[PDB]
Structures are given as C-alpha cells and as structure tokens.
Length: 180
Length: 190
Length: 13
Image 1 (cartoon, rainbow over the protein chains, first blue to last red):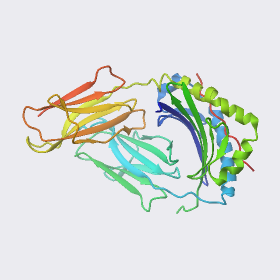
Image 2: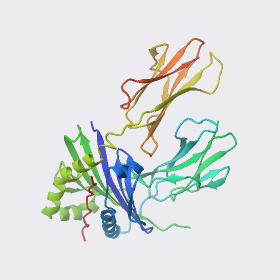
Image 3: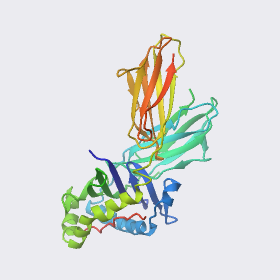
Image 4: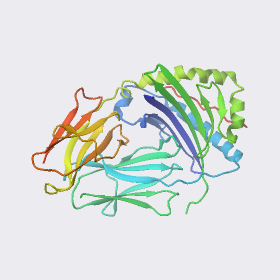
C-alpha cells in the first residue's frame, strides 16, 4: 500500500488577493507561512525546535502563483470557480464531564473557494476568549478543510453554535451543541 | 453583498513514501479552479497536461531540460530530504490514546443500550478497537464513527456496541495502537 | 535540519 504522504500546498485567490503556503503530513499541518509577518508558523510549538524553514522562499512562490493565476484566468476566458458549500460538524475533543475543561471543535469540510467566516456563539452571543483556528488544509479532490476551536467549561446552562458563512451557502449555517 | 466571481490557483507537490523511503513517488500538480490542468509524475519523468488548459505549459516546461532534470532528482533532493528532516516528530510521533467506556443513556438492565468506547487524543491514526462480552469478541452490532482527525495532530474515534445488558456481564473494550506494546482494555460491568 | 521547498515555474505566455 502506501505509508506516508508529505504535501507542499499553496494557492492564490482573486479578487481577494489571498495566498497560502503550507506543508502537510498525512493530513496534518506541519507549518504555514504567515503572509503578513512573513514568518514560519509551526502547527505545534515543538516542531520548531527540531526543524526550520526560510519563509522567504514561500513569499517568492506566492508571487509566481499570483502571476500564474492571472495567466490562467485569461486563458480560461475568465471562467469563475463554482462555489461548493461546506459540511460542518461540531464535536468535543474528549468525552464531556460537567465542569471539566474541554474543547469544542468546528470541523468545516469539503468546500471551495477557501474563504469562510466562522464565529462561535454561547447562548447566542459571540465568544472569542481562547479561540484558535487552522489555515485552509488541502484535500485530494482539491476542496479544503478548516478547523476552529473553542476551549470551554461544560455545564447544563450553556448552548453553543458554530456559525459558518460561505458563498456556496444561501444562508449562514449554525451547528448546535449542548450537554445532554 | 459580495457576488464578484472568484478565480483560484493551487500548486501541490506530493511526496508518496512506500516501505520507509525505499520507494518514493513525487507528484506535482496545478489546479485552476477545481480542475487539475497539468502535472509532473516522477514515474513518468516529464510534465503531462491533464486538461486542455495545461497543454501550453506541459509543452513549455518539457522544453527546458534544466527543469526536467531538477524535477527528476527532487525525489531525492526534496522528498527524501524532507522525510528525513521531519522523521523524528512526524513519522515517529506517538501519543497514547485515552480510553473510556460508558453507556449511552442510563437505562435499567435487560433493556437495549448502546455501550460507548471512547478513544481519544492518540497519534498516529492507525488503531484497532474491539468489543468483548464475557471474554468473547462481539463482531456484530458495532457502530463506529470511524477515524476522526482533530486537526491538532491528534485523533479520536467512538466505537459503540449494541447490547442488552444483564447483571453479571462484563464488557471489555480492547485497543491496539503503535504507542503501546500490549493492548489497552477498559471494562464495564452491568 | 531545514525543509526544502520546490519552486513554482511560471506558466506559458
């Protein structure tokens, strides 16, 4: 069969002017390059103590991807991409026990283009404390995946929702979660 | 409202490893929107257009021996090199799963119930979960969630067993994973 | 150790 796969994935999107450069190992992100700060961001802190990567090379690659997108757009005769709405699922990363720290995971999958707006809601109100997220992960079908996280304290009083906005969706999608 | 059309371009270099790094295949690909247009397959040795849009590029890139040569050696200078660089924390990463067993819904004995075997926080994804009833393996009535990748280099999976608990019965979840020599087991007594 | 990246080649005119 096949034991492992390492993928260097990058993209450039117009008219948003969004680019991304990342390395993937068996579906997990090793690191990506922050375009604003022009730096290598490791998925897990310890990765950086074992290896390195010059962010500069990524910036140069993106410039070329931007130029190739221009060429291809005109060559395709300005054929736009077809929006593919995401499948959204919310789960905890471990079995929930009342008053025991846990994490809600918003899994956004199988969509394109790579642009989404995600917000967490606690009893209907946006929450930002401690939240984090991944960049857009590549898929073999060339669609994308993305994860959003929300550390929280389980209780019978709160309800949560992962609100996702995407152009393939007619209306913002809410995925509900509450203790049962 | 934003309705302006979008144009996406992707470039992917995929290194496929078989038997350690004994066999390696490099796959380079360009995708316009959701369509692969051209690719370089190390097993082929040169670029090939996938769609009509990639025709110009394959012909062009194949006309530069320098590029072809560099690409044909990437299996060594790129793929094998990166495998070695990250081997210690990727290929060799091992995190033991946390196993918990609990009944779905608290129902009295002799009534159908779903026993949940929760396996979380493990890595790599390769794992085996089996249910045992009074020492014997239950191959039927097993409802699995499958492998769930959490996105933080950790996996989880919920394997449930359909049962009709009766006092005296001992149900065991057995888990095999590369992080432990002997399988982990958690018992639930009705 | 350092990660090597493959450089992208410019498309046809």
